[PDB]
Image: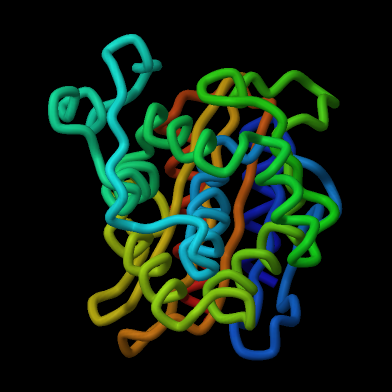
Length: 262
């Protein structure tokens, strides 16, 4: 009971809704949940689904990881720390997904959206793999606006958790694509203070964080002891006036509890 208590206490302390899912990676069944069917802004956690859509195209031969994309300074949107450095040389599709997942690069996410035909086509990919709930409507950085009761650019905790499970371990992607997707997530460099801050030595974690307007904060992860992932955690929150530091700490404390009670 301790973890759902920490979640509810986080809601009270943040003054905001928190959505939570702890899922069994093997059976795909929910172990614990809070607000599983409520919608929350995905923010940068969508970048993992985006790269899954790109990998599905790589498997089908409609895309190639080594393909080079050139772009100009005028394509650069806010928060583009990798893409801003490859203006003369461009970046491969592989480099763009790396930048999008491991550094949350926004221009890399937009260039990859263009390769698949935009937000509506990501939404179509998700629908076709069985997720009729998640939707992407906008590009970076507008997709982080988080207007209350706006369903654009949202998931539910349950839909995101089950979809991540299908991408990492399901029948959709090739073994090589599944491994590349979780490898990018293991190399995340922008989720330091979240679940990773709770992770004991020897544990595996592959994740993707996000933040947006109006207090929006979240994380998707595959994690587990003995160097192997065994469960999927999804945590989202929106609407709080709390600082980034407090939101981070609340997520870390939910992590500490679920790890303590594994």
